[PDB]
Structure formats: C-alpha cells, structure tokens
Image (tube, rainbow over all chains, first blue to last red; front, top):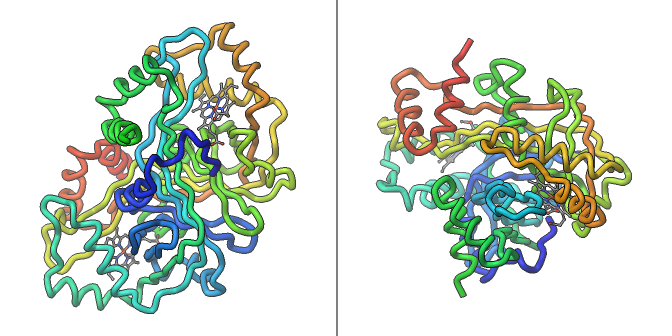
Length: 201
Length: 201
Ligand code: HEM
Ligand code: HEM
C-alpha cells in the first residue's frame, strides 16, 4: 500500500475506527514464498492500531495457521467502504476514472493463541455490540463455544507497523468534489459518510 | 484460503463471473519475504480464471511493483458480497455466528506490462460497460491518458491456480437457511442474490 499525503487519515483514531467497523479481514502470510490469505474476523485490543494487538481465528481444518508456528510476519487488511468514481460524475471534458476507498493494513508477528475461547468470546462481544438487538450468548451457547474449540485455531498479531488509506477525493476542487459526494449519497451512504468524516477538523 | 465442500462453486463460470463483477481487487506479493498488498482495479482476459490473464495498474510512486521485476508469484483477491450472520437470525439457542462471503483467489506469476496505455484503456472499457450512460474517453481524454503515463505502472498476471469460496450457508437445513436469506434480503440484496444463484442447477 502506498498512501499519498492527501489520502492519509485526518486523525490517527480514524484508523482504529475503520478496523473496529470492518472486522471481517484478510489475514495474509507468505507460505513458502507465495502469499496465502484467509478471510476471518479480527478485532483490535488497544486504543491504537500501531502498538495494538489483533485477535482472530480460523478453522483448524484450514492449514493456513500451520505456517504461523514459526511466528512469521503477517499482514492483516481491513477494508471499509469503497466505490468506483466514473468521469461521468465529474462532468469535465478531459478526465480519468479512479476508485475511492478506505483501508487499514497492519503488519506484525503472528502467534498462536492458547486462549481460543477468550478470542472468540471477545469477537462475539465486539461484533454484536452495535446490532439492535445485540445477541447475548446464553449459558447454553457458552457451553457450545467450549465444545467447538477443537475445531478452531485462534491467533494474535502484535502490530509493528500500520498504514491507513482514506482515498476519498479530497484532492478535487470544490465543484467536482461536491458532485462525487452527491453521487455517492444515495447508492453508497457508507462511503459518503467516510467522505464527510475526512473533512471534519 | 480453505474451501469446504459445501462452499465450493457450483458451476465453473461462477468464479469468472465474480471476478468480472468485482474488479477492485487486492494485489498481494512478498516484499523481503513479508506480504504487501495494493488495492487496484484488475480485469480478466479469458473465459476462465485458471489459465487466464489478469491486467492491472498502480502508481509508479507506489514501490510495490518494484518487487515484480523478478516475476515472483502474486496473489490477487477478488471479493464479492459478504455479510455477518448473527445467531439472532437463526432463532435457535445454542448457536454460534459466522460470516458469509464469496471470493476468488488467483495465483500466478506477475510481469510488468510495457503497454500501460492499453491496460488502462481496457480497464476503462470494462468498468464503464455495465454503466448507463457509459463514459467513453474523448480524444482530449485519450491525450490526457498519454500525459499521465509516466506516473503509472501496469502489470499482468498469468493465473496458474485459482480457488473460489462461496460460503453462503448452503449447509443449513431449510428453516435456518430461509431465515438467513430473508435477513440479507432487505439489508444486503447482492448477498441474497448470490445465495439464490448458489442453489441453481
Ligand atoms: C464472533 C463472530 C464470529 C464470526 C464472524 C466467525 C466467523 C468464522 C469464519 C468466517 C470461519 C471460517 C474460517 C476459515 O475459513 O478458516 C470460522 C470458523 C470457525 N469458527 Fe468462527 N466466527 C465467530 C465466532 C465463533 C465462536 C464464538 C466460535 C466458538 C468456538 C467459533 C468457532 C469456529 C469454528 C469451530 C470454526 C471452524 C469450523 C467452522 O467453519 O464452522 N466461531 N468462523
Ligand atoms: C478505468 C478505471 C480506473 C480505475 C478504477 C483507476 C484506479 C486507480 C487507483 C485505485 C490507483 C491507485 C493505485 C495505487 O495505490 O498504487 C490508480 C493510480 C493511477 N492511475 Fe488509474 N484508474 C483507472 C484508469 C486510469 C487511466 C485511464 C489512467 C490514464 C493513464 C490512469 C492513470 C493512473 C495514474 C497516473 C495513477 C497514479 C496517480 C494516481 O494515483 O492518481 N488510471 N488508479
């Protein structure tokens, strides 16, 4: 990921907020020399991505985690709202398209987590908290979680470096920016909201 | 990525259809043995992902492509609709959550593409074709593309292997399945559509 200065986060908390809002992540490691990726729910422990700790899990039957034993470096990609920007939206005569998006990339050493129960229970808590209503695991469901643990592998990543991209057209002039934000208002409310938040100072 | 039998693609054209429908991809390779990823528009040349060729571009100022000159293996991830499955929807008591999603992972050897102009023009054509009205570059815009060319690097991936995941709850019995599909119908119609297509024969 390369992040041009004008697409950097306006405030550092924006990276953590993107991570928390988009927990279904891509966990990537270099099995041999080839990249291999698993889609998995990953949560953040700590106030900031940099220096924070990521917690995730996958199927034990997914052999990806077996490469994690050597504690190699992994990349976790969190992707927020995104959308194609067609030059039709600009209404200007020389133009080229782009794609607007926001993403956080976290890199660090992965470690298998012995407390797989705690990881999945924390993941439930995080993902359900903003739903209306939030699902509260019953005692029966918590005993179920315990019974399921042989089939799951949890892992932790201590974040050594992170980058965040907020590519949200903030380099356009006022009229063209207004057209882009307006065009995303109906079809892509999530992207328009991120657009609004990127200009809040 | 590991693909349980229940979540394998039903028909082989479904992988290529996902790729063509979701061109904003994640291009992943090793840089000093650690994974690095760039978000970029990537198009498919060919009827099938496996054995097909992917074409994409990225900023020249993005250093990711400098690791391609050795022609290492890359992974390109195409992501379709996805959504969290809360146990609230199952309406059963011992339960656990999951996440439903569809994705295609293409692996092969990457090479830098000299005709960067042709790559970006084919990308314009591909992404503007499903839109109405479609944006067709004027001669002025084509001249502008030529002016932009120093800042762009194009690349090709000859796809050696491909995996597709269609994790769409098809393992569920009918009453639990109907509740999952009904709950996505309002909030995530693209995902509901993908579940419908997963049951076709
Ligand atoms: C909190 C929200 C959760 C989400 C979004 C979620 C999602 C997922 C996903 C996407 C996979 C596939 C991973 C892969 O491809 O390797 C998976 C696997 C698995 N998860 Fe979770 N999970 C959640 C909570 C839990 C909990 C609380 C448990 C309790 C032990 C659990 C147990 C398992 C097991 C046993 C597997 C492997 C077998 C299977 O795929 O069902 N998960 N989960
Ligand atoms: C057709 C749809 C297109 C889309 C969705 C698109 C999207 C993008 C994206 C996401 C990037 C950032 C890559 C990175 O982070 O390294 C990029 C870079 C770039 N693209 Fe494209 N592009 C398109 C067409 C074109 C065309 C026709 C040209 C004409 C030469 C062009 C020239 C460039 C240049 C110069 C850069 C680097 C500077 C910049 O980020 O604006 N692109 N494009």
